[PDB]
Amino acid sequence: SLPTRAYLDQTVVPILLQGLAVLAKERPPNPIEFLASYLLKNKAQFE
Amino acid sequence: DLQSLPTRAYLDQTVVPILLQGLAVLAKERPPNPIEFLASYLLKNKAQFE
Amino acid sequence: ATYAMGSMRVLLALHDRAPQLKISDDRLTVVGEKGYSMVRASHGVRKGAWYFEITVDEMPPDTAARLGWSQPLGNLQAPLGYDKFSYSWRSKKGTKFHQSIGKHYSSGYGQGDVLGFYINLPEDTISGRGSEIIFYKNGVNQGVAYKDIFEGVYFPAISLYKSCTVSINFGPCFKYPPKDLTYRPMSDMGWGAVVEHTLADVLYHVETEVDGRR
Image 1 (tube, chains in turn purple, red, green):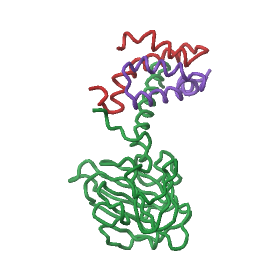
Image 2 (tube, one colour):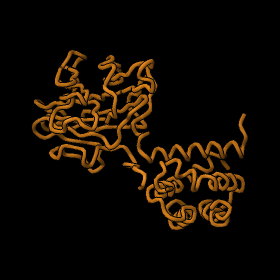
Image 3 (cartoon, chains in turn purple, red, cyan):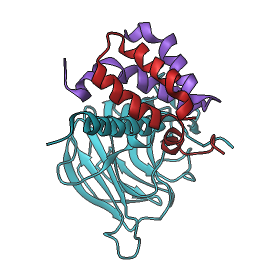
Image 4 (cartoon, chains in turn green, cyan, orange):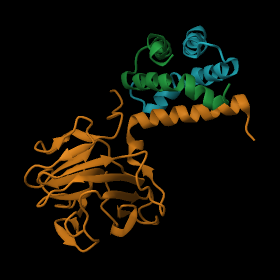
């Protein structure tokens, strides 16, 4: 088990950066839900 | 109103607070499905941040 | 009105360019075509110290480049430095050009050289340190080319004479990062960099919340 920042870098940061980028581009109506849905639809590409 | 905010302020006012707490919870629990855990946290806790 | 975010990354502009220039799919490489013509980057800077690099990929005989900075009104069908809106550095003999006046500056540059482009636009235009344009060749400061420049927004800019090829690197990683000055990479102007900085700051904060700091 890695340090905190290292652990998040290797698990969720890459996909999170992508979801935040889509969020900032499209400014969708329910951003928290939109971001949660984005993480689920794309989990496999980073899992 | 909110679609007109600069990039960082837009994120400030939408997702950063829930992410700030959710990423800390994730870092402490270390569950076996990090991405889905985080997506779950967002959905379970959305109401206190919207 | 949706926020005018511009391009996610700093690239060579899609439409703010001479149509005869040949621009790569990744919009970081450009090939000249006949007489001098110009392309600006997709983001420009108004204040602070900023840096980018250009690599001369190929420069056959009888081709040339004038590289540097341009305000939005700089003429796209003229060499860079043709008018009051741009400042440039010429491959041939290292001349510096502004308002079509060429002045001795450095030795020439050419194929294989990696050139650096520094601009500083202080917040205080009266008692500040003074505005400056500085060129670098393979990591070596070539001196202050221009000072007290026209206030405005300055875009990284490339003008090419005939079929030479250059590639622009806005950062964040440079081949010869200057050792003598501080700066932000031009790539910080892409809204994708603002997203990355926002998350990087949040991650630092999370680390404080979870681990503390010593």
